[PDB]
Image (cartoon, rainbow, N blue to C red):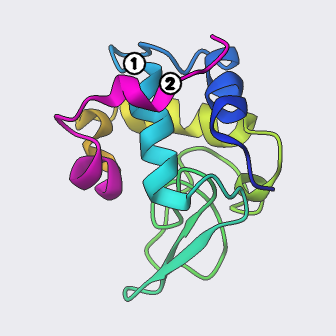
Amino acid sequence: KVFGRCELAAAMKRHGLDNYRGYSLGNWVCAAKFESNFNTQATNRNTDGSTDYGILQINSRWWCNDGRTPGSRNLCNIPCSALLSSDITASVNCAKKIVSDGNGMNAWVAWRNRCKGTDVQAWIRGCRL
């Protein structure tokens, strides 16, 4: 499923997305924009034969079980398949874990690269919020 921008911001706020750990909604929407471009089914495989799933592209090495990842842990305690649904719950609950694992939002390479130190409030633009 592909979320329109405001519907996703919407969904995130609802899951207590904004200012969570001092990260404003804007940061989250931006992260998802450049991680998966709002597609819940997005997947990227990594050389180390690990995989990134969902809207926030969580890694199978440490966060979810996709089986196939050699030296893997399942810190969120869920099948990587869970992260590919239409409801955001699973991705947001996991993200919450990852965000406070000692690197803030730096965990997301795309956020880091494309959202960090930018006017993120733009991502919440014309949003009935």
Asked which secondary structure carries label 2, the reply is helix
Q: What residue do we see at 55% from left, 60% from top?
A: 36
* 16 lies above or below 95: above
Q: Residues within 10 Å of mark 2 (few under 14, many from 20)?
A: many
* 65 lies above or below 69: above
Q: Which mark is residue 75?
A: none
Q: What residue do we see at 62% from left, 17% from top?
A: 13
- Asked if the residue under mark 1 is in contact with the one under mark 2, i.e. CB atoms within 8 Å, the reply is yes
Q: Residues within 10 Å of mark 1 (few under 14, many from 20)?
A: some
Residue that numbered label 2 is attached to: 124
Residue 97 coordinates in the image, percent (x, y): 48, 33
Residue stretch in magenta: 109-129
Residue that numbered label 1 is attached to: 24
Residue 1 lies in the magenta stretch: no
On the rendered structure, is 95 left or right of 114?
right
User: In the depicted view, which residue is nearer to us: 50 or 88?
Assistant: 88
- Quarter of the image with the N terminus in it: bottom right
Mark 2 vs mark 1: give the one in front.
Answer: 2
